Length: 335
Ligand SMILES: Nc1ncnc2c1ncn2[C@@H]1O[C@H](COP(=O)(O)OP(=O)(O)OP(=O)(O)OP(=O)(O)OC[C@H]2O[C@@H](n3cnc4c(N)ncnc43)[C@H](O)[C@@H]2O)[C@@H](O)[C@H]1O
Ligand SMILES: [Cl-]
Ligand SMILES: [Mg+2]
Image (tube, rainbow, N blue to C red; front, side, top):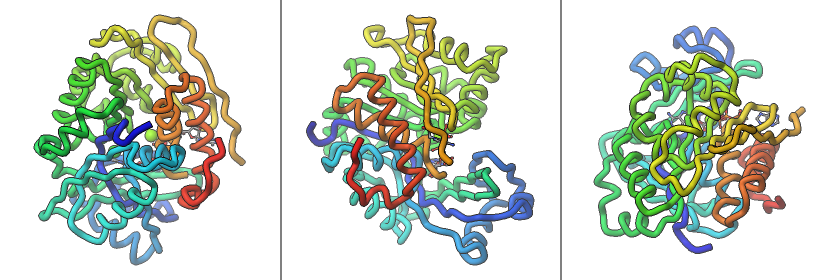
C-alpha cells in the first residue's frame, strides 16, 4: 500500500436528513422510495428541513462516502484521493474535516459562486426519498484535473471509481479518465447510482461502458438500465449477464457486474460465465449502505484480495454502517 492508489471523482454533498410524513413529500412533488435532482421548486425544502424538521447534517455524496468507508477499513491515510467541487462556505468545511479525518486525501475544486451542494434525505416509515441540490458540485471542470499536482495524482493511481451521479456534472471527465485507464491497463469502476442515470444519460452510459471493468448498482438501477437498453426482462441475473457481455476495450480483464438487492443476496456476474454467484446477507432486524458496500469492496481490492473477499468485506461494511452510523468511523475495523 502507498498513497494515492485509488482516485474517486464525484459530487461532495452535505446530507440533510430528517423524519418526515407524506404531506412534506406531496408538498414537493416527491415520490417515496426515489432519488431526484433538485429543481427550483425544491429549493425551499432545505431550510424547511433544517428549521422545522430538526434535520441532521451528515457528510455525504456517493463516491465520497465510499472512499471514507474504504479509508476507515484501510487505516492508512491518503491511500484514496477524492476529486469534486465544493463551495467556500461552512458546509464545505464540514465535508473537508470529516473526509480528511477518515483518511481521504480530498482534492476539492472550489467554487466562489455556488454554495456546497446538499442532498435532502427524507425518511418516511421504512422508505427513503432523496433530493440532491448539486450546486457547487456542478461547478466541477476538467481543468481541475489538469494542474501539475492533480495530473501526478491521476498518473500515480492504480484504480479509478466514478458514480453515475457525476455524469450530471462532468461526463467528459469521467470518460477521459476511463479511456486513460483502459489504455494503461488500470481498473475503471463505476456505479449506476440511481434510476435516473440510465434514464437521463443512456448514450453516455453506452459510450463509457467499453472502459468499465466493474459496474455496481442496486436491483432497481439494473431494471431501470434494462428498460433503457430494451432488454425486455426484469430478471437481474439475465440483465447482469447482458451488461457483463458488452464489448470491452481492455479485453485482458473480464468485466464484473455486482448487483445489490437490500437484504437479499449480493449478485456477482463475470463476463465469460453463465453462472451468477450469490453472497447471502444477514437480514438486519439507512443512509449509504450501497456506498459502504462499495467502500468495503474497494478496501479489499486495493489489498489485491479476490472478488469473493472484496464482496464479503462490502457486505460486512454495509452492515456496520447500518448499525452504528457515523460512530462506526471511531471504532476499529475488525473484518
Ligand atoms: N446526485 C447525487 N450525487 C451524489 N450523491 C448523491 C446524489 N444523490 C444522492 N446521493 C447520495 O446518496 C447517499 C445515500 O444513498 P442511499 O439512498 O442511502 O442508498 P445507497 O447507498 O445508494 O444504497 P443502495 O440502494 O445502493 O444499496 P442496497 O440498499 O442494495 O444495499 C447495499 C448493501 O447494504 C446492505 N443492506 C441493505 N439493506 C439491508 C437489510 N435490510 N438487511 C441487511 N443488510 C442490508 C447489504 O449488504 C446490501 O448489499 C446519500 O449519502 C447522498 O449524499
Ligand atoms: Cl458521487
Ligand atoms: Mg446506491
